[PDB]
Image: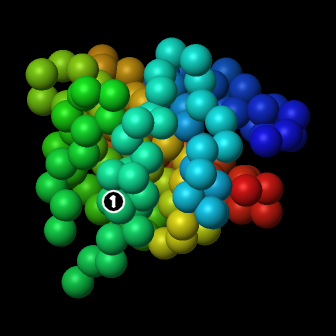
Amino acid sequence: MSEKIEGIIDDLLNLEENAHGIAIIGKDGKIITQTENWNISNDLDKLNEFLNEKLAGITSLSIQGIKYMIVENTEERKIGTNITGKGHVVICPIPIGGTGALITYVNPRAGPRDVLFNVQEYAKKLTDLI
């Protein structure tokens, strides 16, 4: 963790109104940082399993007791939506198809595709820092 990474996250949160939570997984599979409104620590093994699964598949992912149905899975972005109104999650691998990730909890009132432009770009900003 660094203040450079903290600066990037703060910039993303101020820029992207529908980013309601952030977590970063380092290239080693460990949590670098996360926003204080959630904790993904007890779900890290399942998150890493999903992040690193090769496609040619995992259909749901639970984070902190919220079940997300997987509606999109590429090397660039993986999207889960809770279907009881609890929100969405967007996982952007760092690098594309890699072992690090920028994870965004998405405002329940938004669609998860709404944050993609910003989160995919900010994932690329973290390439050399994680």
Q: Residue 116: where, in percent of width, then height?
A: 46, 45
* Residue beneath the point at 49% across and 54% down: 92
Q: In the depicted view, which residue is nearer to us: 16 or 52?
A: 52
Residue 27 to residue 14: above or below? below
Evaluate whether residue 29 shows in this view: yes
* Residue beneath the point at 63% across and 63% down: 27
Q: Residue 3: where, in percent of width, then height?
A: 87, 34
Q: Secondary structure at mark 1?
A: helix
Q: Which quarter of the figure is the C terminus placed in?
A: bottom right
| Residue identifier under label 1 | 50
Q: In the depicted view, which residue is nearer to us: 30 or 5?
A: 30
Name the residue type under label 1: Phe
Q: Residue 50: where, in percent of width, then height?
A: 33, 59
Q: Residue 19: where, in percent of width, then height?
A: 50, 27
Position of 96 with respect to 78 (left or right) is: right
Position of 84 with respect to 77 (left or right) is: left
